[PDB]
Image 1 (cartoon, helix red, strand yellow):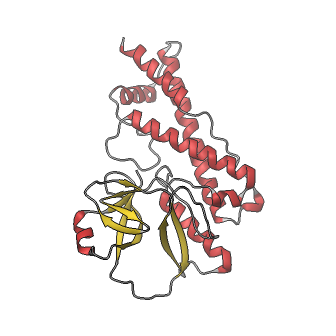
Image 2 (spheres, one colour; image 1 turned 90 degrees about the vertical axis):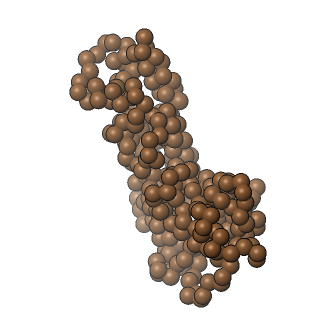
Image 3 (cartoon, helix red, strand yellow; image 1 turned 120 degrees about the horizontal axis):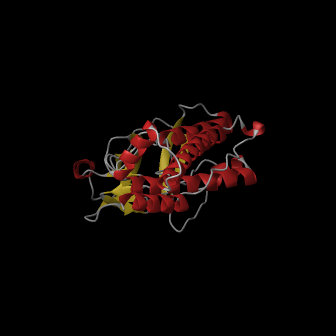
Length: 271
């Protein structure tokens, strides 16, 4: 009855979840690269999580087939899966409050697909592709680590100090990908409350406007006074706002004012 349905949905998840993450992040010549280090640690963590999840869910399928004896940990896991609450063991990256296991496995599958793409790019061209690829920001396990890694990579180029770097963002369209050796194309960010019109904000009644390929560039900070036409939008990851990844300074329209943006609740969201 119920247990066969659990077996069927678990088998569907195994079919949906990609197979073992190719831990091909191995280049002693690329160790000094900060981007390579960050991507290597992320791929290692993702591969270990994939192995644990795949093994546990295959064990669940096979105990559904009835040819094994479950233990206390397996009882806890099945009691977690029956009610749809996320397994506590599988939680190693930050979690929006209360999302179902189906939502979690879909998100984890997306993260494994992008990690597969990252590993293939690294095995094809190394650090260069590790920079040119347009990694999405939402699926990354520790996005702030990615921002720090990009800052370090830009610092190594031209041998600039880490603190001499300030982030500037420009939003593109149609996937221009006109990188200037410091831009970091990133996708998936969703602007809640406004729209971007040639990098100029404007309040819109419709919420959650998708931002395609918001280029991340680090430049010398001139310590000049920011004009009144800029706003500091908090960048969160979940739909709930409980994790500040970084901050973005956007130019607003001539008619608009920062007070209205602060009041309306505008904030960039990765998911």
